Image (cartoon, rainbow, N blue to C red; front, side, top):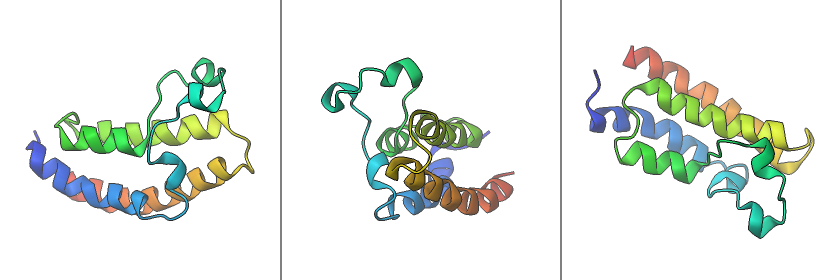
Length: 114
């Protein structure tokens, strides 16, 4: 079992690492709004939207009971972008960078948590 503040402390660096990627975090710092973007098909393809600001709020408000729930949300964010977007699009390429950063940061953290 994990204490919520200790879980948040252990995982925050990996979230910070994502946020610090400039420009690659920028499309992910806030939710995709399909109405503002005029992409009505978005929620037909992305059933469970996720972004860095939502992940932050969850990490901050004790919404992850276990480390894997956070990891799943990070992966959901990535998979949504890789499903919806063209491989050579800015969003898709930016997403691949965040995943590269995340895989490098998360792995030693989960080993210390486990």
